[PDB]
Amino acid sequence: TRFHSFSFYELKNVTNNFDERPISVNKMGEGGFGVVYKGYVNNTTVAVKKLATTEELKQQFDQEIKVMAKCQHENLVELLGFSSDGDDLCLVYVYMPNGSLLDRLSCLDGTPPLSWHMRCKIAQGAANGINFLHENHHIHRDIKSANILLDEAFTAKISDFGLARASETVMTSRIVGTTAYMAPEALRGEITPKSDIYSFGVVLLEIITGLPAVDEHREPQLLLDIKEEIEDEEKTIEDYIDKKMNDADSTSVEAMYSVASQCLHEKKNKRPDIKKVQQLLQEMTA
Ligand SMILES: COCCCNc1nc(Cl)c(-c2nc3ccccc3s2)c(N[C@@H]2C[C@H](CO)[C@@H](O)[C@H]2O)n1
């Protein structure tokens, strides 16, 4: 697939010379080291990711284009174009008005809490995006709620393919990802789609509880450990369900938790593949 060849100065103009301030009062954030700026061009709102070692920075930009050229799906963010003529390298995407699942789970800037009904649809949507990537022999290497973007109708879109790796178990010296979401073997340097499943189980626990993967002022500081308190019969998942929901029945919440439990197996070979995860989430609703 081919993309629009945007000029650096057109992107510099529509993003106000790459301003570092927020929208209130561009800056948005940086998932894979590249400041995302809000922009408007050709009567359509966009998100411009300016990248941002010199060759490793360029390898992050080249992979994104190589992966998105091949990968086209409704549950992945769309790349509209990019820019090479400038000093820095830019990647233009279709703007997502509901931000990340992280910011919507935390109600950042006063947004209403997502209902259980929207949460199930986002879980199913996110799991289609991972299935399409794995079907097409790609490992995301950074599955987290901050990397699940939400469109005009709260449709889950996986994003950030700067760390994406082809498959089509390999080992690596430069270990990359988000500690709070990573699997045991990923933290050791193994590269496998089985790690993407583990990280997705952490996202399901954030969806159910509404608690972020890591909270420094919390006990336990890591969300994945809450699974062990529930397994020891000290607490139940019922006691961790997000209280900012009025439409969450126990059967569907327990059913989502069963998937998150299986996803979070420490033994990589005991975890279910994405196609099984997708079937279980579909059976949950239905
Ligand atoms: C005013 O309403 C707010 C809506 C903001 N909407 C929005 N829209 C898009 Cl298209 C992106 C992209 N971010 C990336 C990052 C890498 C690759 C592709 C993309 S597309 C984004 N990223 C931010 C950075 C962060 C990820 O860690 C998230 O929490 C976001 O804040 N935020």
Image: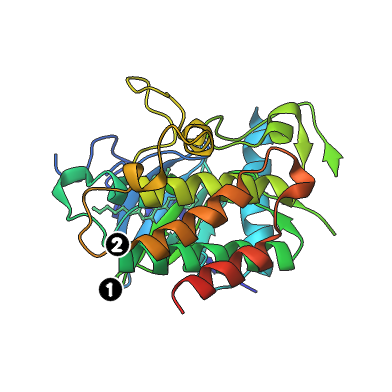
Percent x, y of residue 231: 53, 38
Q: Is residue 242 left or right of residue 228?
A: left
Q: As displayed, is residue 115 above or below residue 219?
A: below
**Tag 1, which secondary structure?**
loop
- Residue 92 seen anywhere in this rendered image of the structure: no
Q: Nearer the viewer, residue 68 or 20?
A: 68
Helix, strand or loop at disc 2? loop
Q: Nearer the viewer, mark 2 or mark 1?
A: 2
- The residue indicated by pointer 1 is 43
82, 9: nearer the viewer: 82
Q: Which x, y percent locates residue 238? A: 35, 48
Residue type indicated by callout 2: Ala
Q: Which residue is mark 2?
A: 248
Local crowd size for mark 2, using a 10 Å CA cut-off: few (<14), some (14–19), many (≥20): some
Disc 1 residue crowd, few under 14, some 14–19, many 20+, Cα 10 Å: few
Above/below status of 159 relative to 86: below
